[PDB]
Image (spheres, rainbow over the protein chains, first blue to last red):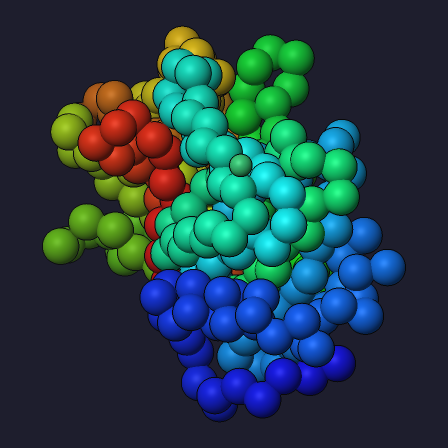
Length: 148
Length: 148
Ligand SMILES: [Mg+2]
Ligand SMILES: [Mg+2]
Ligand SMILES: [Mn+2]
Ligand SMILES: [Mn+2]
C-alpha cells in the first residue's frame, strides 16, 4: 500500500513519531492484521506491520545503514541487545510503548505474546539486513541479506 | 594495472589465486610501494586489490566486508588473523610469509600483531565499497558501524 510521507530520509526520532502516530490510525493497518505486511516502501522509508506468534524470533541482526523504530500496538515482546561474553540484555516492550535506534544497532526481537502486533519503520529503507550466525566452533559470521 | 580476470565478481578461491599470482610477479608491485607505504594495484567494478606494508601497532579492529569476499597473501613478515567467538575467547592464527588465506562474504575478522615491515597483498570482490566496524559501548553492548 502507501502512506503519505515526506520525500526524504527520517531520523530516529521521526521514525518513532511515525510508528506511534500510525498506531493511533488503525485505518492504516487494521485490515492487514488478518505474518508481516508492508504498509509503505519507497526510496526513503519502509513501514511494516508485524503480527507475532509466541515462537517467533528474528535472530540477531543489524539493519546495515537503516535507522528504525518500533511501536508495540498490542501485546508485548522482548528487545534484546548483544553483549560480549553472552549475557545479553533483554527488555520487555509492552503495548503502547516504542523505541528507536540508529544504524549501528544490533538486536533481536523474540518472546512475543501470542497475537502481538507491532509497527516497524526504517529510513533509509531496509534494503539490506545483516544476520549473525555462530558455527559449532562458536565463531561468529554476518550474512548480508537483501530484503528489497 | 589492468588484470586479465573474468568480468564478474570473484569468489574467495579466485581471489586467493589472484593475490598469490601477484605476489609471484613483483615487477607489478615493487615500484608502487618504494616511496611513501601502500598502494592500490587495481580497482574496477569487480575487484579491489591492495598492497599493504605494516607497522607493529597496526590493527584493523573487528570488521566485516559487508558483501565482499577477500583473500590475503603475506609476502614478507607475519600477520595474526583473528576470528570472533561468543564468550570472548577469540581465535588467533599466525599467517606467515608465503602463506595465504581467503574468506567468503560473511567473514568477521581482525588483522593485527604484524611483524614490523611486514608486506601483504589483499583482494576483495565485489569491491570494498562498505565495511562494518564493530565496537562495544559503555554497557558492553556491541554495535556495527557501516563505513562507506
Ligand atoms: Mg505489560
Ligand atoms: Mg579491471
Ligand atoms: Mn530489527
Ligand atoms: Mn578485513
